[PDB]
Image (cartoon, rainbow over all chains, first blue to last red):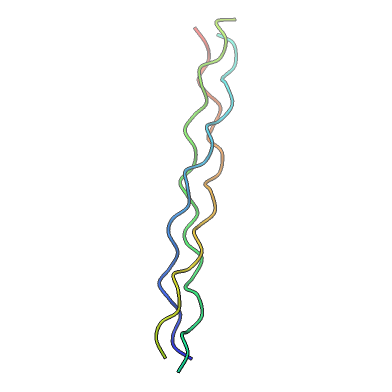
Length: 23
Length: 25
Length: 23
């Protein structure tokens, strides 16, 4: 069998974080 | 000879952006 | 034998930080 293929693509960016605290 | 295995798992993505601003209060 | 297929896409990034304080 041949060698491994190329590395996978980079993952999606994470979800946005939660809303900040009250001002 | 047959094809080799799949390549390596890709890199994890970048962290998400900060959340929205909090409530005015 | 030829190279295999591209690897799996990476995991989604971690969630972002909390947002800034409100106004």
